[PDB]
Length: 113
Picture (tube, rainbow, N blue to C red):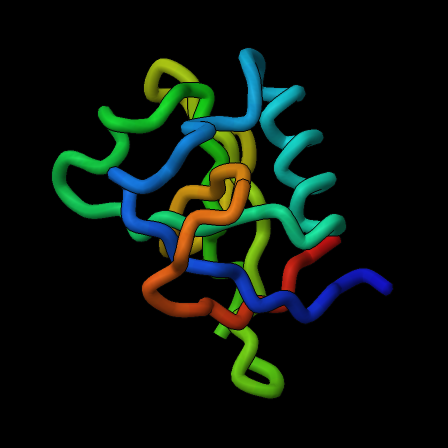
């Protein structure tokens, strides 16, 4: 399928144990997609002070369109040293590995896969 319905645990930035997906734009997009397929991906809502507490390159979920079955359609965009790889809409959050942190909420998304 071109899209997959996922419910992503929303994590507090200070709880995150693994603060990024790897060391290159291509690696972080690859690992993010793998963790999304395996159900081991969390989401941190971006506010003042959040990104400096995480590791670059960053992987964002961004709104791809204006929401089937309550699932916002999203795509992945990576960022390294202020340059983005991908073009999309508003940031829903930054993706991180999930390793059993307790979420504060869930974010229903339709991931372009």
